[PDB]
Image (cartoon, coloured by chain):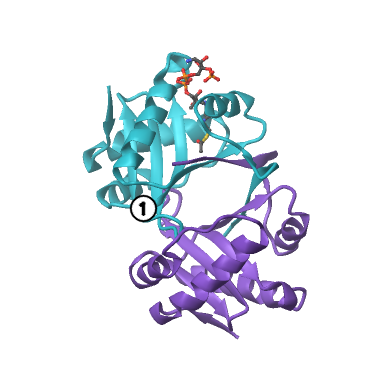
Chain colours: A purple, B cyan
Amino acid sequence: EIRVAEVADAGVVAKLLRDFNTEFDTPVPEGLEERFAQIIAHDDAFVLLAGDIGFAYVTLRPSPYYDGPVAMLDELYVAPAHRNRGVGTALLQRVFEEIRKHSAGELQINVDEVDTDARRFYERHGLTNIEQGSRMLLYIREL
Amino acid sequence: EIRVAEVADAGVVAKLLRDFNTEFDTPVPEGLEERFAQIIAHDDAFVLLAGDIGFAYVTLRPSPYYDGPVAMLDELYVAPAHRNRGVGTALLQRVFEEIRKHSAGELQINVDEVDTDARRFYERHGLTNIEQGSRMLLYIREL
């Protein structure tokens, strides 16, 4: 079942993030558990856990467009063996429920263009890459 | 010169965001000044002002990958008469300087695909849309 992670869940959340990066051949940094523990306790953010087979990491940040925050689904992951079983749907449905408690004006997610499975999942559940008749692109600089 | 906005600057910031949305036929919510006043008062966001003809709005949110926050350039705007004069470059350089004071691990910007001029501006100043050989997309749902 889906539940809101507590500080003591930081080890499981960090373990899942490590599998996410390992699956996609991405090096992971040290101290994931200690940082998740501090984030879950203090920051304007939360983690949802689907047992220990999936998680969603959501951050909340201010916007002049709404009284509430803008939510960002920074990480959404379901373990490969438990995919295509409604877990991702349940996690995302709970994300919308939780951010609605904060009166979040909008949910945002960054997605790779080549991840067609994830894009179709998000489009099937009400998210769009289109604003004002244009695709939206994410630009970054790692520092 | 370019300065960090204070709460007393919320009026000029809200006026510039209004002009930004007005120029691009984007709806403007009520209460921009009062929301900017509250947002500027707090520590997870800031506004850089280039006199009264340009601004940058940056939010900071936690990440498990860095001790510092992930920075997001949510708005970057220069008044039409003052464009192409290096004001945007100076604002973006100040953005990098300010977020470095927060030990920000990454800067993120959402850019419309059609805005080829802004895309070239960001690309000339160290921002990339490519990750592991794939373009990066933003998906949203307004709520």
Q: Quadrant of residue B78?
A: top left
Locate residue A90, reporting x and y percent: 65, 76
Query: Looking at the image, how many numbered discs can be counted on the residues?
Result: 1
Residue behind mark 1: B68
Name the residue at 41% across, 55% down.
Answer: B66
Amino acid type at image mark 1: Gly
Where the N terminus of chain B falls, by quadrant?
top left
From this view, report whether residue A58 is shown above or below residue B39. Answer: below
Locate residue B59, reporting x and y percent: 40, 47
Relative horizontal placement of residue B67, taking residue A119 as reference (left or right):
left
| Direction bottom: furthest residue | A1
Q: Nearer the viewer, residue B74 or B109?
A: B109
Q: Nearer the viewer, residue A61 or A68?
A: A61
Name the residue at 72% across, 72% down.
Answer: A80
Name the residue at 73% across, 54% down.
Answer: A115
Q: Nearer the viewer, residue A18 or A6?
A: A18
Q: Dot 1 surroundings within 10 Å: few (below 14), some, or many (20 or more)?
A: many
